[PDB]
Image (tube, rainbow over all chains, first blue to last red; front, side, top):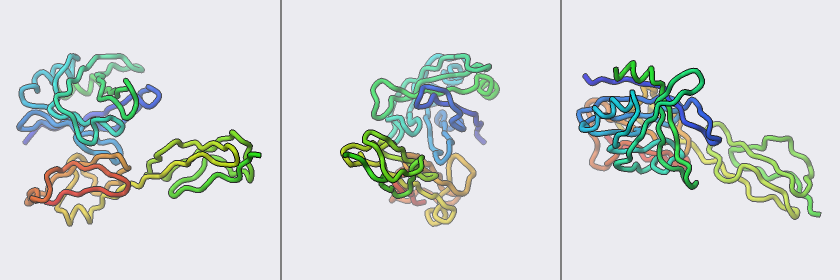
Length: 132
Length: 123
């Protein structure tokens, strides 16, 4: 019934380097979108958003810009991961990495460091492929 | 003075090196946890005054098994994987199987593994 697709994703690691993280599943819902992160023994909502912002998202996720999340969780070292946080903006920039061009976005800050947010990238071609 | 003997053992872990029978003050060794265990604490202990600094700890993972997903009437929301091994600090999220609905006892479907204990929702 609903448009589903999944895509691959990376986070910069403990030394600020990029690294295969796992899968980002992206599911269309009656109320907007839920994205889920499959990454080892972690498979749980990564973040989600409301119908209002879908359109924006679809653009942002294929040309950068920003959009507000209904719920943002992120991934295992982020502060936001266990409880979730609301209305977290998310700014995507297009940035080249190795031979390929990627959508990148900062995640939440990290426990228990100071000023060390997380970062993610997703292949612009896998995104453009799916969100046309 | 003030040399240490072998580094202490830790449940579900090991050192990365071969144990000397004696260490010089200020020497380090380093611990690794078993496959799915999460090391908590500094990984590297240091010898001083005849004593080893505090060792780390290996946090247990949680086995999400087909059997238990049955009893609770649930299934993994994001993978088709029928079983899952989750490391402390890792979130899992379920759904009900077609037919059941979320028991009054549960309010959320998204849990996190903490040190071998993971709170399942009931459907």
